[PDB]
């Protein structure tokens, strides 16, 4: 499988998941219908998205790591799938929620070859491959901000901060893309609990890095070794190269 | 002027502003074209929105209080207008920005009779009159959340906080409506700077109050006396009755 397949498989998945969600009323979306393999609840929205996405993905030679059903298949290509990131917003009719896919040639993130995050409320398409990083078919790159007085996405602010603004939209895979296109000067998830799972971050990190961004765990270590399994957890620090060391210091 | 008019006029404005903003590309939206009377810079997006809003509004017996052009007209009816709330999001293409109006029979908030907030990205229409509060034509009400372990919108977290979820979207007039329909259990703007202006909050407060929520200033006092002028500033604490006093306690 190559980056071209992945882009085609992702489009197909994005379409069906956009249908399935659009067709499901809010009151239905919010029902708890099961336990996820990740150990969080599966809402009726998640299940309906994952089923649509899995229908298409299992037909490929892959192993899938997905929030609700867990680890499936035995292929050499691994796919980190958040069938629905921002499930809370989707249950409330808040227009920031996405399906997110990262394809890797290995169970480690450093062998990623494709990232895909698709906003299910607006149809904004972010993805990345060899050619670079794209939003709705147009190349996206990060910002050049040098000052700490920047626009920040941060989970969670818990002290005074020198930021011009802080924002928290409740869809990590999409907010990583808000950073990748330069909308925001950085993405911080410094929650000491280390909450983010591989299917939350992977696509977003890949897109951000291809868009030029410096992306590392809470203390600057490559994310290359993060595994495509359900056990994996992440803190993320992400900014342009000039600003990144500055943030690393700040959150010490 | 009655609440029926205000609806008709607000909807007529929403349309024009949806169009004008829609046909203006991001790269154009973000240009600084002037200094607003409010003392913040006017982006090209603000200008086109406001110009379209005022075109319609000044045909009415009103005094308008607006972010970019300040105070206009001499009507006994005062309208607090944010021609574009969430200007930052709009310049980036994040589907959370609104036009916002609050009509009042006098220059104090207590004499409000119509509230209106329209998301210019999704077309979600919030409003309220005597008959109650509506989102897309269907009635809404605040949540019944009792515990501090609730979903919160907060400007700005700088502490430990017992919330289940914190979010910050960048459109106060829209976020007060996310509160009003029970998407979030409370809306907190506790910034010591007292950053909120009458046209940011007034529509949102009215809608939230009609939807059942208790909305007060930082210390519990009524917002009744807030003036329709450029000078005026606000902190907000909004929640259902059971939760509200718990939150007042929580912050100090
Ligand atoms: Mg779950
Ligand atoms: Mg979930
Ligand atoms: Mg201004
Ligand atoms: Mg402005």
Image (spheres, coloured by chain):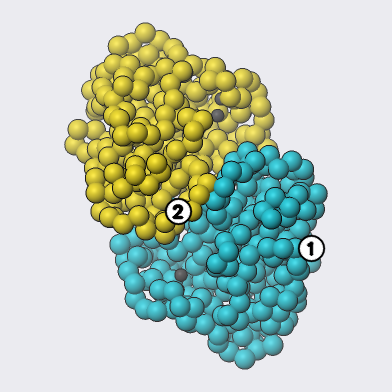
Chain colours: A cyan, B yellow
Q: Is any atom of residue B227 visible in this view? A: yes
* Left or right placement of residue B104 versus residue A243 in this view: left
Q: Secondary structure at mark 1?
A: loop
Residue B232 occupies quadrant: top left
Q: Secondary structure at mark 2?
A: loop
**Quarter of the image where the N terminus of chain B is located:** top left
Above or below A229: residue B63: above
Quadrant location, ligand no. 4: top right
* Left or right placement of residue A225 versus residue B216 in this view: right
Residue annotated with mark 1: A131
Q: Residue B161, labelled with which disc? A: 2
Q: Position of residue B214 (x, y in %)?
A: 27, 40
Q: For the residue with label 2, is its CB less than 8 Å from the closest atom of ligand 2? A: no
Residue A26 occupies quadrant: bottom left
Q: Nearer the viewer, residue B109 or B217?
A: B217
Above or below A25: residue B89: above
Q: Residue A40, labelled with which disc? A: none
* Left or right placement of residue A30 versus residue A166 in this view: left
Above or below A130: residue B34: above
Check chain identity for marks 1 and 2: say if they share one.
Answer: no
Q: Check disc 1: other Cα within 10 Å, few if <14, some if 14-19, many if 20+.
A: few
Q: Nearer the viewer, residue A140 or B142?
A: B142
Q: Which residue is the extreme one toward the top?
A: B74
- The residue located at (40%, 68%) in the rendering is A45
Q: How far is the residue under mark 1 from the one under mark 2? A: 43 Å
Q: Position of residue B121 (x, y in %)?
A: 49, 44
Number of marks present in the image shown: 2
């Amino acid at each position: 499988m190559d980056e071209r397949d992945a882009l085609r498989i992702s489009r197909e998945i994005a379409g069906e998941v956009r249908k399935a969600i659009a067709s499901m009323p809010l009151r239905e979306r919010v029902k708890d219908v099961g336990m996820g393999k990740d150990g969080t609840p599966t809402k009726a929205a998640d299940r309906v998205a994952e089923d649509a996405a899995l229908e298409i993905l299992r037909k490929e030679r892959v192993t899938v790591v997905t929030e609700e059903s867990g680890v499936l298949g035995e292929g050499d290509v691994f796919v980190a799938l958040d069938p629905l990131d921002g499930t809370f917003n989707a249950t409330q009719g808040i227009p920031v929620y996405s399906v997110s896919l990262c394809f890797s040639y290995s169970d480690k993130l450093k062998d990623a070859f494709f990232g895909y995050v698709y906003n299910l409320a607006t149809g904004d398409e972010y993805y990345a491959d060899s050619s670079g990083a794209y939003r709705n078919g147009e190349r996206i790159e990060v910002s050049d901000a040098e000052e700490l007085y920047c626009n920040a996405i941060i989970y969670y602010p818990d002290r005074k901060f020198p930021f011009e603004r802080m924002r928290i939209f409740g869809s990590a895979a999409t907010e990583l893309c808000f950073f990748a296109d330069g909308s925001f000067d950085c993405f911080l998830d410094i929650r000491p609990g280390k909450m983010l799972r591989i299917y939350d971050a992977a696509a977003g990190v890949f897109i951000a890095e291809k868009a030029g961004g410096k992306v590392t765990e809470l203390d600057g270590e490559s994310l290359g070794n993060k595994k495509f399994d359900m056990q994996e957890r992440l803190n993320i620090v992400a900014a342009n190269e000039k600003l990144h060391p500055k943030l690393l210091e700040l959150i010490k």
